[PDB]
Amino acid sequence: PIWKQDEKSLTENDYYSFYKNTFKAYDDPLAYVHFNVEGQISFNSILYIPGSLPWELSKNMFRGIRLYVKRVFINDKFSESIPRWLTFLRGIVDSENSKMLSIINKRIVLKSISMMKGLKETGGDKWTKFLNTFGKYLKIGVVEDKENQEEIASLVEFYSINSGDKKTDLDSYIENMKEDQKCIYYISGENKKTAQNSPSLEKLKALNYDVLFSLEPIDEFCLSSLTVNKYKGYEVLDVNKA
Amino acid sequence: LPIWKQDEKSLTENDYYSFYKNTFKAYDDPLAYVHFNVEGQISFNSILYIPGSLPWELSKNMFDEESRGIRLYVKRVFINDKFSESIPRWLTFLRGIVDSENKSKMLSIINKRIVLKSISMMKGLKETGGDKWTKFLNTFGKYLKIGVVEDKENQEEIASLVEFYSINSGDKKTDLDSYIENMKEDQKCIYYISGENKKTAQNSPSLEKLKALNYDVLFSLEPIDEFCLSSLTVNKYKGYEVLDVN
């Protein structure tokens, strides 16, 4: 019924208490979205981004989402039915009516990306916290969700030669690209320090080009996908390849 | 120092409204504003306002050949008020300031950030605003319709904001996503029909098969409604074809 109620009459202690007691979570979520939709195909959903990594996920990256059909509880195993890069979301979907699992899912993915973009726009510690905690899942989304590849990739961030102590997003890298520069460059390292000290790196340093760092297999997985598919038309080259 | 260099946190709404009025010599309160700062190579401050009513520069022709609107400052000195000549012209109605530290691949960066902040400002006004949102579309909706035609890169986001009367909508307009929401089971298309008046438009004979399908149909009542709707007719709207009933 919580998700049946009006979303001009519900306050956030309502949403937080619901989340906290349904999901057994003492963390304040970073964000939530209550959406009802709407006419012929018919459903309500509340989706939450946890304030911290769920314990079950702290040891194996892949409940999440509780399905109700017609206000009856089916399973809390509906996370299994959405793209797995979204397994960190917690929430409900209550559907009246596969070719519905399909369009329910498209709508969930849309709303979750929109939630993240909103959180990024606000910026601050909270966006930083979000990428710190869940950014690995986005990086997986970039490869695995072909249709949303460009929007998800616009959220992920990496260390680079120039970003120093903080990470850069890809769009900032683009805006920072020198007059002659055609491509986005990256290089693998054991970590920040070893990576920037790679003598690979001297021709690009001579050109004053930035280079992103790939510091873990998931970075490699994500970036190599961008080499194939490009990012916003830009080539993405591994400095130790061709 | 100037308002755009002060931290937004100490400022009140009235501080922003008084600045808008004094600077642009405008009488009515703005409908909305956003103050942002970008820090890096890269460095600029901006405050962007949606006016309360049509600027006088725009009250004769839809477009002012001079494109005033946005005042450029460099290192806090006023340069000129023609910075809007480089932003998409569908945003000519915005009034605001940019103060930069520094067709360049750079002015281009500032322009892009402005368009994105302007869209997010409108989308916020749509989500929060109810009466203010309808006021915004009644005054500046024509510009958004032109944006849908002319702004290739932002076409879908702008398209999501525009509203039209339909058969089922009543004395209120519907947006496209709400139309999509209301589509029948095997309805695949968004339909529209050139009308003369909101009343006369649904009286059309050419509507019989569609009404016999109980499909909604949006009304085009001017060449602007008409060019807007026809541009969706070519690269679709969120994957939907948009068909003229003729």
Image (cartoon, coloured by chain):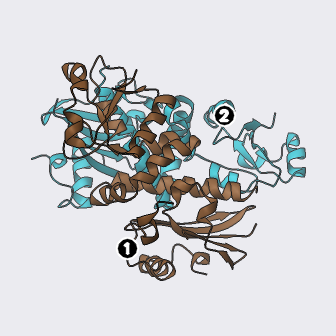
Chain colours: A brown, B cyan
Q: Residue furthest top?
A: A180
Q: Which sits in the foreground, B228 or B195?
A: B228
Q: Which sits in the foreground, A124 or A59?
A: A59
Does dot 1 land on a helix, a strand or a loop?
loop
Disc 1 packing (10 Å; few <14; some 14–19; many ≥20): some
Quadrant in which residue A176 is drawn: top left
> From what the image shows, is residue B177 above or below residue B226?
below
Give the side of residue A205 with respect to residue B203, left or right.
left
Residue matched to label 2: B226
Disc 2 packing (10 Å; few <14; some 14–19; many ≥20): some
Q: Nearer the viewer, mark 2 or mark 1?
A: 1
Q: Which sits in the foreground, B190 or A79?
A: A79
Q: Amino acid at mark 1?
A: Asp
Instruction: Please provide percent x and percent y for residue B74.
Output: 16, 31
Quadrant in which residue B47 is drawn: top left
Q: CA distance from mark 2 to mark 1?
A: 48 Å
Instruction: Please provide percent x and percent y for residue B120.
Output: 42, 48
Give the side of residue A36 with respect to residue A128, left or right.
right
Does dot 2 land on a helix, a strand or a loop?
helix
